Length: 160
Ligand SMILES: CC(C)[C@H](NS(=O)(=O)c1ccc(-c2ccc(CSc3nc4c(c(=O)[nH]3)CCC4)cc2)cc1)C(=O)O
Ligand SMILES: [Ca+2]
Ligand SMILES: [Ca+2]
Ligand SMILES: [Ca+2]
Ligand SMILES: [Zn+2]
Ligand SMILES: [Zn+2]
Image 1: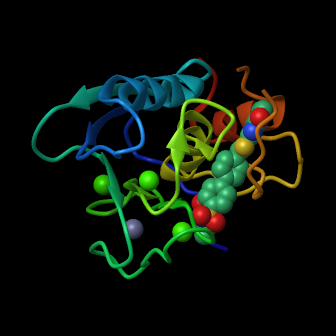
Image 2: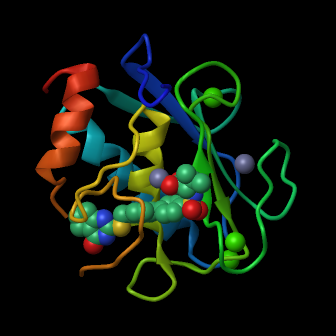
């Protein structure tokens, strides 16, 4: 307790509030869209992007103290966090812009980190399977959602 939790609805919205200097707008948008599709492809979840106003999953880049009780720490250490399902900060995902975000093998691959963090946004906890997306340690192995993660998200939301 309290490891997992699910949204009471499956039509979810998201908003990209701001953009990292590290990547182009298009690269950031592609990364987040692909990261949501990881989860919608195997469940009844569907994700719609909003360009303004409140969305369920608010996405932002920030440094140090950025508006919650979970400050970032400069280069290294923490790279991102996401709140469990619920109102207000619930579901929101924050990325530490004192890290280097990429669409490549350098730095942290934004797609891979976002896909993991959106798992947390949807109520998943970590896996003990080193091959799982939800494993606690970041690696870059070169995308198909591993079966451990498929089982985890389908146990909350059912299959697609
Ligand atoms: C609980 C908080 C404190 C923590 N924040 S953090 O900054 O310490 C943090 C640490 C690690 C991660 C991360 C990102 C991507 C991954 C998959 S990497 C990966 N996965 C897969 C493949 C791959 O190549 N790489 C192939 C299939 C699955 C694994 C861990 C994110 C954030 C957290 O959010 O977990
Ligand atoms: Ca950091
Ligand atoms: Ca929210
Ligand atoms: Ca950066
Ligand atoms: Zn935060
Ligand atoms: Zn995690």
